[PDB]
Amino acid sequence: RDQTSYGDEIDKFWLTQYVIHRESYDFYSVQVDYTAVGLMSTPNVAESYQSKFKGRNGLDKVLGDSETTRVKINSVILDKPHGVATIRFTTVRRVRSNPVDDQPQRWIAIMGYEYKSLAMNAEQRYVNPLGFRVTSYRVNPE
Amino acid sequence: TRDQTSYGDEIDKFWLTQYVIHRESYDFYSVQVDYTAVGLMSTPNVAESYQSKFKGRNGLDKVLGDSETTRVKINSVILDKPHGVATIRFTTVRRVRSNPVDDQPQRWIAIMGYEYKSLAMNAEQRYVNPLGFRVTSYRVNPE
View 1 (cartoon, helix red, strand yellow):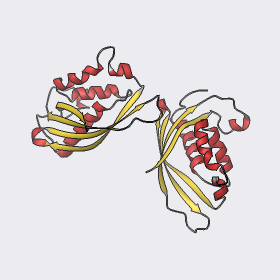
View 2 (cartoon, chains in turn green, red):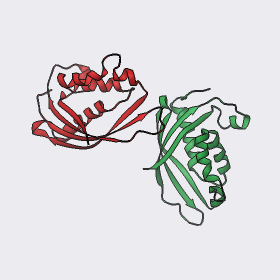
View 3 (tube, one colour):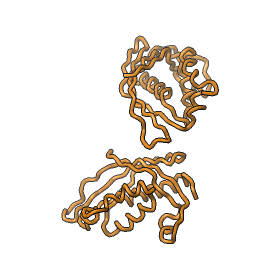
View 4 (cartoon, helix red, strand yellow):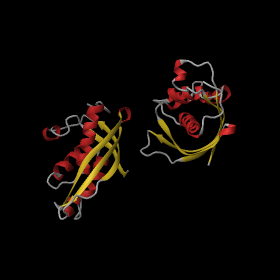
């Protein structure tokens, strides 16, 4: 169904799922994450994101399993009538060669989002059943 | 609650910045609250100059609706407490909902006259303007 929002708790779920999928890096799940971000984006948002994964120096082809970045959501502020969200989160990167994790980094994600009923199939349905999608996405430091 | 020109730097600065934020912002979802607030915090002369733009078929909220929004950033406040005069430098960022980006920032100077007046007040005004703060003159110019 086409609706801008599904309520505070549902919106926060898909939005945090989006940031977790897009801003994390783990080689063992990057294909799933990449796929998810693709389904949860407008083609403009998606193709701006998929750029990073193309060419000989695509992110996963450069990094491999050398490092990881995990995400911690700190807060989510919703503007449900306009499909706008501001999400503060923290990244902790870890290079497998190093013995310790790197120092945490804090970010702000300003997001536009919406729900669209579109032609969907079973494996996509199993990922994005409500047809959630991000319509704009920008990250800046805190 | 009392006829006073000033209440001290920190309190004066609070009401003055609140006034500018209420008056120079535009948000359809809060415009009724902002409009009410400016009215309670103004002398009738200052008020009816402000309420003018909201009157008629082409009242600001009737024309703009929720099509666009304008947010305020206070940059600096200079107080002249004995004379109830303040200078406030602020920045507005307008955003048209049809556009993908915000407009470019605009910088302004607000020269304000202010005072506090105990007047006959009700519960709803008391919850908004408890000290009877009011702006006695108001003019904005670009920077």
